[PDB]
Image (tube, rainbow over all chains, first blue to last red):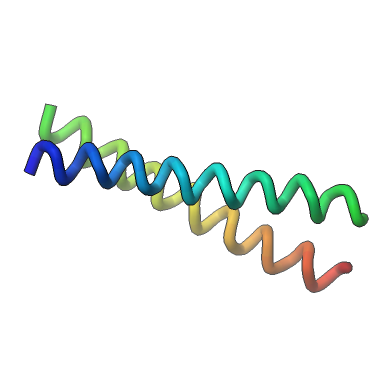
Length: 30
Length: 30
């Protein structure tokens, strides 16, 4: 459970990074 | 600790949603 929360923060960090890369990209097609 | 981790997850999830919506907006524009 502590591990499950840890893994969870990790996952969301990843997804978050993806989302910011995409925005960069779209921000460059503007 | 347990509670900090819980707080990190909530904060990250909020960011994620903010990014997904931004993302959806940009694409609409390009």
